Image 1 (tube, rainbow, N blue to C red):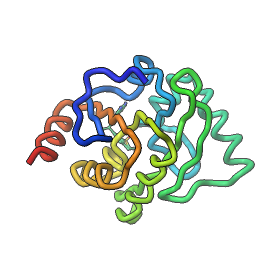
Image 2: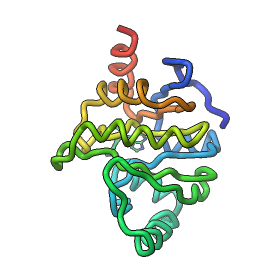
Image 3: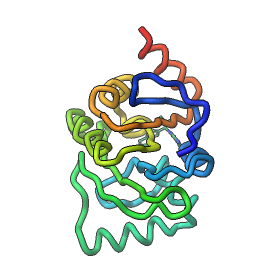
Image 4: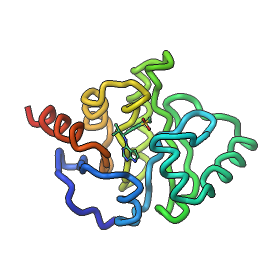
Length: 167
Ligand SMILES: CC(C)[C@H](Nc1ncnc2[nH]ccc12)c1ccc2c(c1)S(=O)(=O)CCC2
């Protein structure tokens, strides 16, 4: 959990402009969060990047979990191996607003983080999931009580998020 160069927002929420994959290699976190979908198909974005960094081992393990347990629910999660990126990967399904899912489920999605003492995570439901990223940060700060290190891979968005928090 050797996090470096983060800006502390609250006593339990930190943020950095960085690729979560690059962070997981630098930090060696106990938990890395994946911004998953309900069938754990890691086809692009954050999930595709984390899977590629495991040379597809994450996808094979994910398909086996879905075979035995069935899909996740929106707002739910599961704990699987972290492979070479972390001890564990917490796969969390935030709502995809662009596909009609309820933004209120973003609180349930962040609540999964509270079962783990320290996490490296992306900004849930941002990017192509369509949630307003300033709203996602506000839900993160109001919901997560354990120690969360957010990696946001875009300097323009990072600057807007820090300026919004400090208003
Ligand atoms: C807002 C983006 C800059 C951010 N991208 C990232 N944030 C941190 N490490 C990253 N590695 C590669 C991309 C990447 C982001 C955060 C959350 C979501 C996505 C994107 S998505 O994949 O479009 C859909 C799922 C939710």
